[PDB]
Image (tube, rainbow, N blue to C red; front, side):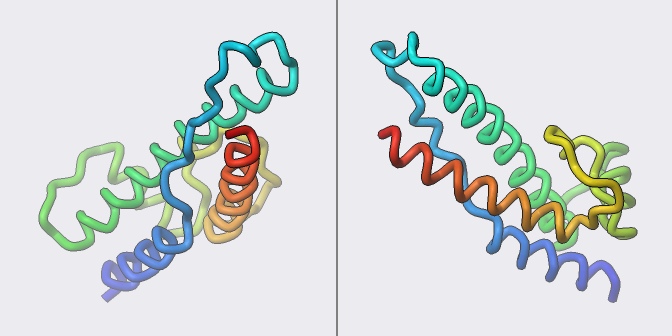
Length: 123
């Protein structure tokens, strides 16, 4: 019932959320560049956050499928997602108060898309 709806919306988000952020910000000749340094650290943080979010959402989907055992952290995460309140761990950038998980993931997807564009331009 509810758990299946959670699975469906998590699968929809995983389809919506772009895949692994290409951490192609790597040039020893561009280290001295300030813009390169800033974009490198931003892409690194975005890629780590993307990996964490993707793995957590895949874990949520798989435990919705029933073929795994959830732990205390997963219980906290599912209790956060059921009420629509943003997961506390996923918060690595400033978020307006009251933003729903759907709004947060849409914003995160847009940020990941623009970071993909930045990495493609840098490469």
